Image 1 (spheres, rainbow, N blue to C red):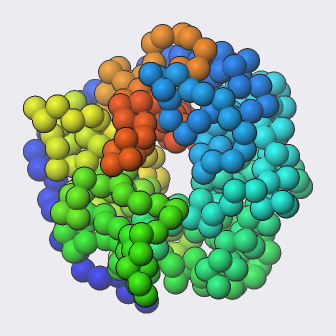
Image 2: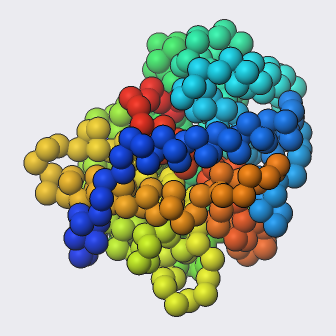
Length: 378
């Protein structure tokens, strides 16, 4: 078991992070309060239902438990609960959990590429918090559905955390091996030797026919999809928790340094990393929020003697500060997102320069991470 060698770029002009002011308790508190205000407003708006993956003119539409993104809404609720302990949040979120348990029992609109995202921030999340047996039941069942459908995209590094959890609850090594196998399979096949992320085959390897499930994400075969990069930056340290393989840290350094080096002047990624300032292209804030979470996670484990550790700390503070000051929602209206200016799917023209629910979740996760010693759902 070994990861292929990648180019680890040195961090270019580190002082553009190191000279930043660290976010204070007051700054993060207020960013949280502002997010939660919008969350409480959207609770009346959604009821027991869910937001759409992305907003339309910066307003979400209401939908049922049928997409790949529903767990992120419930995740936001559990994150808010971490903060204020408001039982209202735990009541509503648990009603999402029961809906998720119903979903996996009846196999409604289920795809194995998405089981991690749907059940970790919703159901595993509740189990972490209060040990609810229905939330455990739905998570284990979602993990068992993931095992048989394996019996390859960067996204999967996040998905396999569901398997690591299954192994910890059951003791069954078979969950762990699949997770380990798939981590290396993803690292060696969805990461380029220059540390950029790329995709699996978009076409059937037998016939060449167009595939249904996922179509197009980056700008081109030569580009660097920003969220794909971000999936790696967070997916790696999550797997590293369970694997303690030093090569994962090196892989993290490669993927993160690649990301940091292609950030514009305000340190918020464009939707693809070949774009920078003066391109007119939209930003992807959800990528930047995701990267902050990954960097924050890896810093728990990165040795004090790593020459880039302090730069990583200041980099994540810089990216988050910019997200708070320049990209967070100010308009207190029903249906508005927590975070503006993401892009869902550029090629299909879905959610371009719009708020998205994973972006809202990861921005809020980053705030909670900074503010408190947060026990991970993942």
